[PDB]
Structure formats: structure tokens, C-alpha cells
Amino acid sequence: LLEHAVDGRMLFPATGTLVLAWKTLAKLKGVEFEQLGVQMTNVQIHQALFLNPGGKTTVSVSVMPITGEFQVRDGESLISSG
Amino acid sequence: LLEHAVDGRMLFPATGTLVLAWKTLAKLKGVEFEQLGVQMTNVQIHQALFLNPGGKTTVSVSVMPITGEFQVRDGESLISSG
Ligand SMILES: *P(=O)(O)OCC(C)(C)[C@@H](O)C(=O)NCCC(=O)NCCSC(C)=O
Ligand SMILES: *P(=O)(O)OCC(C)(C)[C@@H](O)C(=O)NCCC(=O)NCCSC(C)=O
Image (cartoon, rainbow over all chains, first blue to last red; front, side, top):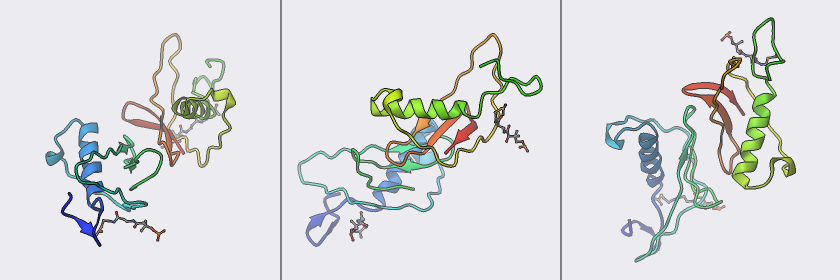
């Protein structure tokens, strides 16, 4: 993930919030993420996680059980929604 | 809560889900629910909840941290939203 930069700065991909919501619904459904067929709609990105070499960055996903609304919150600030 | 029936049907009050959502937000915030000023919007009572007299009913209120989307549910059935 360090090999994805934009003008030197190292950003978290915009498709990383899809594989994070897709790996959190699979857990919610008790299935392996590679055996679940998902369809995310109206995915929005409000900020950009700033990676850093030799460091650890944490992010909290939260998928609403029935309806299917998901967050990728990083504390109190939203990094993505859909 | 059993002293509220509609032609013999003992239903859970529509404002019952308002308090459950109100108390859940306070528990998420850590504050006491009586010290919290809330505002629910578009509270749909998706389906009716028939309270079981002389028994116990379970709900699974869920509030999204930042957006505020709350949801009262029982198993895989939706009972409220907003
Ligand atoms: P201002 O114009 O208010 O800034 C809005 C920003 C922060 C740009 C926000 O709306 C945004 O789009 N952030 C970046 C989204 C992102 O994660 N992009 C990186 C992955 S895609 C790639 C080719 O960069
Ligand atoms: P169908 O046409 O799908 O029926 C929809 C029903 C079952 C009517 C559903 O919308 C429903 O039960 N809504 C009522 C929720 C409710 O009971 N609210 C008030 C609490 S009881 C009271 C006023 O005594």
C-alpha cells in the first residue's frame, strides 16, 4: 500500500474502503469474504487516510446489519461512507 | 407496557422505539440519557412488535456513531428506523 502515492504523498486507495466494507459484511454474515457477492452503491469518500512507512494506522468499519449502511470511520472523522 | 393495547392486540408503543433509540445514543456517548438532548427524524415504524404478556421480548437497537442512523430490530426483522 506504500506503492500508491499521489504527488509524493502516500494516500489510502479509494478502493480500499470497498474491500474493507466487503470484509466486514462477510464477518457480519459469518462467511469468508471471498465467497460473498456484494454490491456497494453510492460510495463516498470524505477524507483520505495518510499512510506512513514503518507505521501502523487503524480504522474502524461499521456495517449496519439489515439495511446495509457502512462506515469506515477513523476515530470521529469519516473517511468513507456508502 | 401491557396497559396499552389496540382491540386486544398488545403492541409496543410507537414512541417506545423513540426511547430505546434515545437511551442507546446516550449509552454510546457515555452520558446519562436524561442529560442528552436528542432529535429523531423520519422515524418509520416498519412493522409491529407484539409484546408477549408474562414473558420477555428482546430488541437490538443499533446507532451509527457519526451519521446517527438508528435501527430497532428483532432477529432479522426490522421494527423501526430513522
Ligand atoms: P477540499 O476540496 O474540500 O478536499 C476534499 C477532499 C479532501 C479532496 C475529499 O473530497 C477527497 O476526495 N479526498 C480524497 C479521496 C481519496 O481517498 N482519494 C485517493 C484514492 S484515489 C487515487 C487515484 O488517488
Ligand atoms: P401491511 O400493509 O404490510 O401492514 C403494515 C403494518 C403491519 C400495519 C405495519 O406498518 C404496522 O404494524 N405498523 C404499526 C406500528 C404501530 O403499532 N405503531 C403504533 C403503536 S400501537 C398504538 C397506536 O396503539
